Length: 223
Length: 163
Image (cartoon, rainbow over all chains, first blue to last red; front, side, top):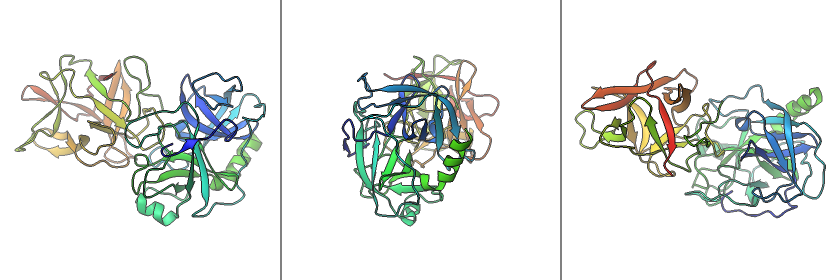
């Protein structure tokens, strides 16, 4: 997260880290046994870490739960970045506490200009690299689909939205992928991609979760 | 699908670090630039015996993940991360053919993938994303090995973090 702030311990309790010996993606806990993340974060033998604020130390409030099923969306297209969503069924229920809680799915899609909370442990710099120890947070508005399409010609589908600042300086970044975009208390986005980080006229692009709610509900119901 | 790995067993980073591409069959030769046609400046990417370990590269994906997988479309560049110079592309040019060259623009999604081959990795070029790839190999000319499309005959590299 570039141009953000330290979330604090209890502030983003639905944030999880996707781990295979190292942190590589974010994710969101949507109930005690299911996490949503990005399809491009798919990896064998994922461990989900929950209750973490400082990713680099064993604070004790952590829970490390192995994935039992990692289900990439069946239309995920690695050529076009479309349908960039994955569900992870955890092998056991997370125990919920002050640092571990679920985020609920939206009942409808969010509008342009709505302020959202974007979080992760990704790069905090627009040029060069610096990775934080603690979870970082950013308030960023949804951008209209027209300006998202003007920002990235030929690449924005109906299953993506832009959020952030066309001025630059504030954005998600590498290491934030798969993490939450929460608007009006509901999971509306998943960190996916962009051109650089926090660059002028190159906002973040996020998987549009409101389009997938029926797929998520069905998938959970059948698995 | 697999994570691309360096010679120390660590995942290759998305832009953050530079890496030498160390050929397994031409150990005494490193990445450099050379002139192709009637061009004034050297713009062709070559493996040069008088240039070892050679110029290091960065691998870049727009995806907000900090590692590179074999399935990601990549830009490959010399020089710094957030720059648009030293960006590899493939350009038809005599006498080399489909020659790997450097340019000063960078698309959202680059045309390359890094794919496991034998004891290291090959660079594969995609004219378009939906299609099969074309291996990058070597054209021996003027006592250097010009990187060019040579499908079936890839130059196999190990990826050594520059440090």
